[PDB]
Length: 60
Image 1 (cartoon, helix red, strand yellow):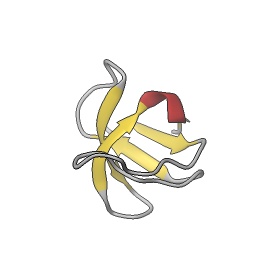
Image 2: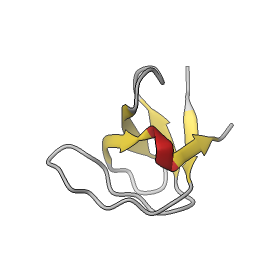
Image 3: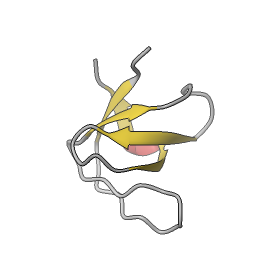
Image 4: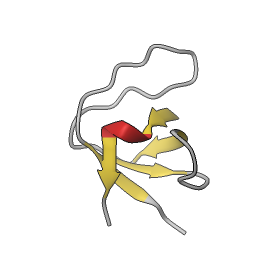
């Protein structure tokens, strides 16, 4: 199923595989919410990559 989140803070990409996002973006994960880093897709930007769980909160 869909598992969505909204970003609470801006995050700047620092690796080859993470995802930059801004506060307020809607983000979905492409596996489960286990662990601290999730492969995600931004509904806002269309970009993808790993995001840190502690920058986002659940969004229905």
